[PDB]
Image (cartoon, rainbow, N blue to C red):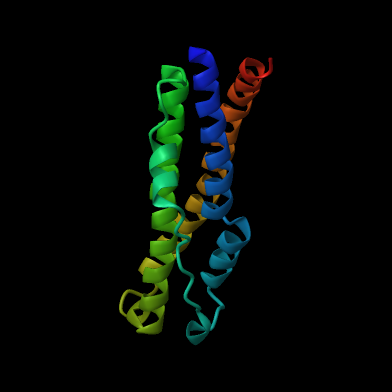
Length: 153
């Protein structure tokens, strides 16, 4: 009864996680942004690539896992989502900065120092985005199986 209601909340959290992680971490878009950071890309060819904006209430829900999860699972989910939201922001904001700095010829003033700083950081962020997404699914799928046990009469 108290476990049945907790199990229903785990299913809601998993379903929201599935939807939000599909739209937030767009692997092919991430790869396309890395290609746009290439040294041989014509500066005037750099396109605008907007950050995906998912449901804000879904973001709040997954960012604050309830006490139905163990304190350890709750902390690991909260940490990985927090890092994932900050990393998403950095990845798309760094590309916006990069595009404006290349197109207004600011790169000539610092001999591409900011271009190389951004390229290195974007590569690290791209790996980390896929890592946080997989870590969240890996925490949840055994708990989800546990919730299915509680919900199968």
